[PDB]
Length: 405
Ligand SMILES: [Ca+2]
Ligand SMILES: [Ca+2]
Ligand SMILES: [Ca+2]
Ligand SMILES: [Ca+2]
Figure 1 (cartoon, helix red, strand yellow):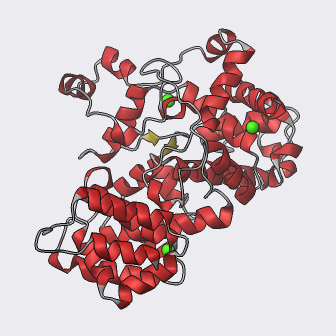
Figure 2 (cartoon, protein in one colour; figure 1 turned 45 degrees about the vertical axis):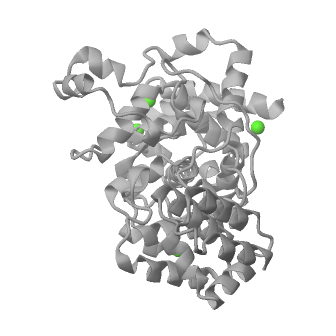
Figure 3 (spheres, rainbow, N blue to C red; figure 1 turned 135 degrees about the horizontal axis):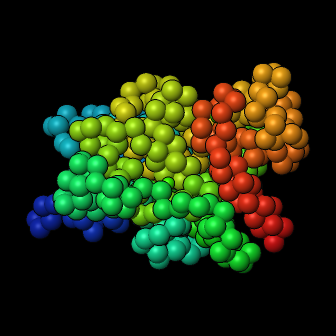
């Protein structure tokens, strides 16, 4: 193909030219991504013995990641040929892609994640690129975590050593610095205009996902909204309900909290923190296999705890995890006997347990309120979160209003 022709030239050596430079590698990657016949291109490269050379010669891990994610993402019928060539290419024991943010994924696992993600994105309808909807520039206070800013938790600088020492000694002032920013939830909402609220919601859903696998997508990363819609369809939810849960968490989130969430989880301590958009707890993601619909069993079986924590920092994995767990909680609700949940019935008298089995568009508002309690706290133990239900319900009202807009 025209693309394989160019790639063969770019990776070749000459009288001069004893290396595939970073710029040549970038051109190769762009050619792969711009290609209208990617399977044909891979077939041609393999036939000429150039496929293994391609993987071996694109050296810096950051470029290897882009190359491998792009090829895994674009291939269908030649998927196996690419994977096999990648495997053969690693015989001289390169770092491959296993560095930096991706140090918890072996190189072949990186390929397999990208293949599964691209396939999921295609099948579930979130492959298509979103606009560069604007992120918040905030660096502290409520609504300054990744939901607002698009700054990935895995990209945040190491917490200052002085603070790590204070956090270790459980210093009140420093703990607060890295914890939930909101005390009185209702007081927080009371200080926002309707327009402020719609703005937050739009900021959250309108911007591209902060993803650890951007080149697995055919173009630019999809909007949060698109991924939330895909998850809503997969789990019989709505983007308004998923968005309400996430907007509540993100209002009660800061940049510093994000840094602590991630860094503690992958430290030698392997802390069980809540991570990312939906503040999914690492243990919950493992207990309930929350990536089931984006990653195959072979990939999931091999994931380390720290790999799981890292995936939770990738917005699309987090949105699917959040949504799958919401549907788990709703399904569990539908199996309950309301007579055995007198505190729940007391607090939410219009709760309809059977309705939980269906779509949120047909849920009473009390179902949204009760589920908010039972998302943040243990589900259906008849112990309720004090203020989370009205906090999420207000965000829900906003999404119904935004949906209105
Ligand atoms: Ca938080
Ligand atoms: Ca797979
Ligand atoms: Ca509970
Ligand atoms: Ca909307």
